[PDB]
Image (tube, coloured by chain):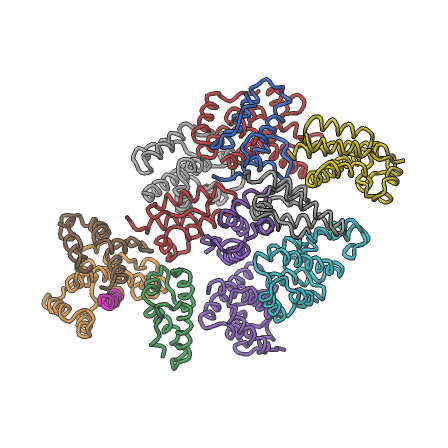
Chain colours: B purple, C cyan, D green, E yellow, F red, G brown, I blue, J orange
Amino acid sequence: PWADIMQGPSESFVDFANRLIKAVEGSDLPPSARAPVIIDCFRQKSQPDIQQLIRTAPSTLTTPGEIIKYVLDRQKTA
Amino acid sequence: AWTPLEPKLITRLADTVRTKGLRSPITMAEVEALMSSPLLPHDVTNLMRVILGPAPYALWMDAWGVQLQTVIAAATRDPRHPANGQGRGERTNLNRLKGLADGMVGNPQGQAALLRPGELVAITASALQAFREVARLAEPWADIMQGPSESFVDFANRLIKAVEGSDLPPSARAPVIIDCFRQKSQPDIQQLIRTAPSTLTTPGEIIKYVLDRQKTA
Amino acid sequence: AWTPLEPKLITRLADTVRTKGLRSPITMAEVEALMSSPLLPHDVTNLMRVILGPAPYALWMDAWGVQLQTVIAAATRDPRHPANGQGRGERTNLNRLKGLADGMVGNPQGQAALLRPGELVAITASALQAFREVARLAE
Amino acid sequence: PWADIMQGPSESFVDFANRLIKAVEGSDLPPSARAPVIIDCFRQKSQPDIQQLIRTAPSTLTTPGEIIKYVLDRQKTA
Amino acid sequence: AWTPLEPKLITRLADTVRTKGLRSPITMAEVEALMSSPLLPHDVTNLMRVILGPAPYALWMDAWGVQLQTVIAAATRDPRHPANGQGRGERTNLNRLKGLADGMVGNPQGQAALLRPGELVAITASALQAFREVARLAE
Amino acid sequence: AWTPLEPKLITRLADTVRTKGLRSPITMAEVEALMSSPLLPHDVTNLMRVILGPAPYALWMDAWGVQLQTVIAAATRDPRHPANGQGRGERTNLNRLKGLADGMVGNPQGQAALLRPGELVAITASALQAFREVARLAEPWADIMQGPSESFVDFANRLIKAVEGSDLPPSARAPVIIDCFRQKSQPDIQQLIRTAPSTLTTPGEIIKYVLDRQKTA
Amino acid sequence: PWADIMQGPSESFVDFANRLIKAVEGSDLPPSARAPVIIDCFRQKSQPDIQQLIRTAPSTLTTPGEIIKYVLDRQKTA
Amino acid sequence: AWTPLEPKLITRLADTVRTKGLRSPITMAEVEALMSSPLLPHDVTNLMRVILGPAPYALWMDAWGVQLQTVIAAATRDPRHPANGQGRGERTNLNRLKGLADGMVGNPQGQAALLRPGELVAITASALQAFREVARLAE
Amino acid sequence: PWADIMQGPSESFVDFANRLIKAVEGSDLPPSARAPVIIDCFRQKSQPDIQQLIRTAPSTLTTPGEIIKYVLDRQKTA
Amino acid sequence: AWTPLEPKLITRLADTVRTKGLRSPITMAEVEALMSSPLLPHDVTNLMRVILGPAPYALWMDAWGVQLQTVIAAATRDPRHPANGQGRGERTNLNRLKGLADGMVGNPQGQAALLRPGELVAITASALQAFREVARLAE
């Protein structure tokens, strides 16, 4: 179930994005509703450090690929 | 023929002034509403007597006199005033503007008879400006900070209120509001505005940008 | 001839916006109610000045300008706009929509004189959409 | 009674002026004696901060409205 | 007539990408090998769906769209594109490049029918450049 | 005939820019001094090459181009520009302003030959404005308070410096300086300004009044 | 000696002014130098409460009588 | 023809004002030295802009205006002012003294063209007296 | 050597730009290869705060002067 | 011819002011008594010097100057002042009222020579009003 996917405390972001995109594209949603759902799940899941990282984006991110690129650039190396 | 204003509207306006105050935008809108048709000096005088307290009424009489004197100076500086006439016999004295001239003292019917429509609109605009002055006088922007727990829209509302209701010229409010958004508005929003890939040149644009990219918490 | 909106209705609408907020369906219904007859730029501008706070009013001015610009782009994309005319001399500039054109600045009577009914309804729809945007943005 | 009106330690000046003008105009004085009485009551009542503010007026104030305007301009914001 | 790529070659390429990674010169050589004949949007899309993981596939869709948009800008900047024609009725829209146009959605046979060879080679070069970008970005 | 600027003056100006910086009033005065006679594009270009570092020189080239483009827009908006002529054959292109036109590239003598005096003064004013922009860019007023032990002239100097060297429009500096004198400038001077029997409508008048009636300590 | 006159900690201001004007007028100064000396002695003597009271005078006091009147008006009743 | 003052002398005078202050007799002597030839309003204005800080410069502008107003009152009190002429068409307005008149704003060459030597010496004496006042006031 | 120039942790950006432009223009590169090299060195050197500041530029910067102006405008005052 | 006031009456008045004060009705009656005949500026000045202390004397000089200035304003507002004359050559300056004019400084005989009776009564009334002001102010 896509709506139950959370980014674990120790999980990296690319694994979380892979799992989420997999569960969203392999589901019962229409094809035209996958990108907005993936974006809004990146924003509300993806534990509050990345949540604030996406929130304070000086540019407007309108695609899952752009969000992934931005987060991978500005992520807290740890 | 003179028709008085409804005491119901006047009572509602008086209670509006009593609860909201003199300076609220709703109060100024209501005054503009009851200032729609050109009023005779009797009407405006009684209106301000009823809606204003004693001390604001004294202040308003002073300010109205000063504004009418400026109007009469402009009138003697231009013989084409809609209150004036072409010959010298139609020059309008302050006794005719304040309703003190002959055949007008205490009588609204005679007032409405002898007065010109240009006279009426000039008196009305003068009274409105005097009301604005007294309202600004009866009740500091550079001391406004965004509190640690305060949201940004409340801070923006408070700051824009204090800047527009102050002694600055009209052409100096937007730059001051912008530069106060940048230097107040605690360092998280300060850095959010600083790192703006676009150049924000308006308080509305800054507010929109900050509301978009703000840290949801 | 221009007739102003009742300050009683405006006061009631302002208190509605004050208690219920900008986004409640009752508030949007009340705005639609007071947005029934085509309003002149003066009317809508003063209405938003009274019912909205300072910061929402700035946001609303921005959004209204953007929506009016989209309308003017559609107007230059179609010479059959109810605001436009057939010849090029009736093309509607943003100074005429925002009430900034000659013979209109600060004067609602002259405004009502020179404006078209299509102009009025376009301005009104633009203002309503801008109000919706700002309400969705404020909260 | 107008001659018993004092500006309270915590009262603002516009409230004091309203109360005083009310009590003076709604009294048994002749109409031609209200303005001088209101002025001289502004000067002797209206606790010593405003008393000194009115005393050190570089201009001569000859009307209750002018005194009110001057005091509202130069009052100690607090 | 459309002929699919061998699932054996695709499986070998997928395991190559799995062990060597996206950026190794051997992997890019293998991709160039399987990118030899001009592929239809269906072929490249399924190929990237199989060889790439979910997140690299999203990145690749983004990059492919951007590169195709640059191609279409160059095409509207030159009416002599091998994908374009001489008249205005042969101008190539992004729905025709991404395989979204009418008569192409989900059908590779119709795709191969309506597409031009210049269209195919442009799509292929765009996909290769997008793969290079995503490979440089992922690691 | 073209005469070069003295390398002694240029060396002194370069050392002035090196020690005082780009924004000091003495530096701007020195630049105005060496910007007295109308200079050819060659002169101003070499001058900025010598006195400015590499990055400020790049910024200055950008700003000079932008200002010259604004000048050329005003020139195509008015055929009576002192750089233009009456016919269309005297219209001035940016290649002629930047010294890139034919017969001018690298040759100051030919430059001085073909250029107009209006062209020279326009180029010079453009270069001065560009220098001002870059100086303001290379290196907060609403955070300035008068310290408990600081004198008033130091506070006024600091405040006027920070307000005039900021992003405010020129017509908004005096009201901001006044309203910052009134709200900053710790409550003794605040009350001293508040209880002013006269109305002070200029920073100089406020400074004079406060210096007269200040508490000697 | 006029230049040795100080206002005592407990002395009133009218006594100090009387003593100072007496010692200045009954001295060897020219007649045209008594008023400036009396003023500048009011400003520098007359212990720091009255010193600050004279310093913060919104009007310019240019006569010993005017200074005396101002100080008597705004003095700290004690 | 207008010749500017040396920036070397101005820099030395500025450092003198910076170390010795505004009121030292050496500073007043140096100012009298640089106040020897009759200066145009442009020269004195820029000189005070450079040597004085912001707040002393504001004070000096005020004092200079007041002294020039006293000069203009004396000028309207005597038609034989070396700045005035015999007829009424040569009466000198404060816009001509402060350099604000037509053909003078920002242009020192035109300034030097239209100004009289009596005008120059009156402006110079006024500026010197204003400097003395501000120096006595600052410390 | 231009390719060894890094912006120090405590160094300002104008000093780094001066040093880099000096070393690039005083080197063996052709004249037509200096601007692209200076730009690409601004992007890859100039420690990751300014790197991300240049990366997230809503406009396309195609000149060292424009990059310098943008960075000087939006730099983190510290 | 000038005749001085008796030092016996002046001593009695000084002791009255010393015991009863400045504001007692008996003191004001005594002052009115010694203010019966029109006095020359010399007489009133010496009288106030003797009966008043130093600080009340300074206050009285101030108040007397202010009242005389009001009198001179009324005099320039009416050419029919008993101190004035019909032509402009008889206009009365404050130097003539305060006894500072030419031929009067320190000499009471010349004072009595050049002064008018209207001048004397105006000076006397001014001095009486100033005494009243100072008496109301001192206590």
- Quadrant for the N terminus of chain F in the image: top right
Would you identify the image quadrant in which residue G17 lies? bottom left
**Most foreground residue, F27 or C103:** F27
Of F141 and B187, the residue lying toward us: B187
Tell me if residue C133 is in the magenta stretch.
Answer: no
Q: Is J16 situated above or below E69?
A: below
Q: Is residue F140 shown above or below G46?
A: above
Q: Main secondary structure of the magenta part?
A: helix
Residue F9 picture location, percent across and down: 46, 23
Where is residue J52 shown, x and y percent of the image? 17, 63
Name the residue furthest top: I28
In the image, what residue occupies the spot 67% across and 22% down?
F102
Considering depth in this image, is I69 or I17 the residue closer to the camera?
I17
Magenta stretch in the rendered image: J121-139
Task: Please state the horizontal and vertical placement of residue B178, each as a whole percent of the image.
Answer: 54, 49
Q: Residue at horizontal 63%, vertical 29%?
A: F97
Q: Using the rendered view, name the quadrant where residue E79 is placed.
A: top right
* Residue closest to the eye, E66 or B29: E66
Residue B201 in sight from this viewpoint: no
Q: Splitting the image into 4 quarters, where does residue D77 fall? A: bottom left
Q: Please give left or right for residue E98 compared with residue I37 in the image.
A: right
